[PDB]
Amino acid sequence: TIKEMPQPKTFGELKNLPLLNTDKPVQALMKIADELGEIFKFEAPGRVTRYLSSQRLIKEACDESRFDKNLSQALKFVRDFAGDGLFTSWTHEKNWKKAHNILLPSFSQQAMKGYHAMMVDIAVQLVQKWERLNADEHIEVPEDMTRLTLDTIGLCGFNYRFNSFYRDQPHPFITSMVRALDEAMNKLQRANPDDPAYDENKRQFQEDIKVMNDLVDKIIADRKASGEQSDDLLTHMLNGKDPETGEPLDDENIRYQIITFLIAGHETTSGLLSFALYFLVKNPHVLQKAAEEAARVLVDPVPSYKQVKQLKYVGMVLNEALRLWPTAPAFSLYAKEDTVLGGEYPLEKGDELMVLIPQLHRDKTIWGDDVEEFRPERFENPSAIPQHAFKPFGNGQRACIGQQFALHEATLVLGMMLKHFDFEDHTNYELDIKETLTLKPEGFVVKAKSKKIPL
Ligand code: HEM
Ligand SMILES: O=C(CCCCC1CCCCC1)N[C@@H](Cc1ccccc1)C(=O)O
Ligand SMILES: C[C@@H](N)c1ccccc1
Image (cartoon, rainbow, N blue to C red; front, side, top):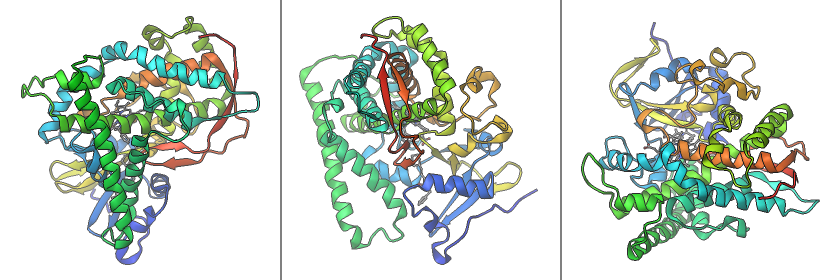
């Protein structure tokens, strides 16, 4: 039977917009979802969004015959610097399928064998940093995880060393990319974006886009001018031809792909690693079981690709961290045609949906009563998890191309962390989640006591 959709409290002509006038809009939407349930309508002047929280409805939203990836307003603002890269392109843009066909082989489980040595290079820099801390000192977790994952995708992406472990102040490119992401997300909250109040914001945004284009376009030009054939994503993009069109990517699109990969490495994997370590220090029995696996498997000074594949429990820890705090917390869909969601909610062609991944992952009909508990054992058997219950990498053909890359890096790094150190939650850290494009545990600090195992 056709149901009226719940809607949170309104602010006259501003409708629901002021509810997201916060530095934590995703956590605000999770609290709305807790109050209103599996679906709610969110209205702003000239905009309707429907927020889905239940596996019951999200399993329908994930039907690619009925729904396609939508560019959320957030992604439309990110598109001002990520262009028609894979992340901010519509499925129907020629450059989406072309880049997708060219890059899939670069992102395969098989390509990970090739990236492994460069991931180890950065992972060993992280371990060495922590081995070199003095007795009184602590680790700034998301800070060090962001140094790591930015550097990894720099090196694997285009053989470029951001040298993040040599620095306090980020590489200039990163200061521009972070400020551009911040501007993109802040613009969601401007009820009148064309105010001159926001004129300095507009001008900084253009300068930041230039910094990004200049380093990346110079990186591409330098690579073309050298003729060097390093086994990185830039080489694959310069030489690759789409089997369908027979065309290569042009230099502008390659720039967008590189900016996109840097956004991904900086924002996502670092969040996952930060949440995984958070849950391990809060669940000492789970930390011990993961530490036991790392010690049993990582028998060599340098982990091998094959050894990373054997860190099953560490992979379960990462999936459980993705369940409770999916660092990429939402994706947007549009109805390809008029359709009825869940037998109750009529949608028109073009109607926009937001999938609230943290809420999906807390659906008690799927996960049961222990849903807030950190239990990696939930992930022992992928076949025992219902369809579309677990979506930290999005859905279908528009799912994360980087999923294998991210999980290989996170497994390697967390394996080495658990092999080399005992960890202390010395401050009894109270989770405080900072929102950019992604969720990260802000101010998360630990102490690492070396097990004194040489590299
Ligand atoms: C834990 C780490 C990561 C998470 C949680 C994550 C999550 C996601 C999600 C949820 C999407 C779908 C977005 C949407 O539907 O709007 C996505 C897309 C994408 N991710 Fe990731 N990601 C991660 C790591 C990476 C890495 C390391 C890369 C690249 C090196 C990457 C590249 C991409 C790209 C290119 C897309 C767009 C794919 C397409 O539509 O063709 N991601 N990611
Ligand atoms: O749900 C949100 C706010 C959380 C986005 C989180 C999302 C951003 C991309 C990367 C993954 C996480 N935004 C919607 C609806 C909207 C539109 C305009 C103003 C306010 C809300 C949108 O961007 O379309
Ligand atoms: C590029 C993609 N991995 C992503 C998706 C959602 C948030 C940030 C990044």
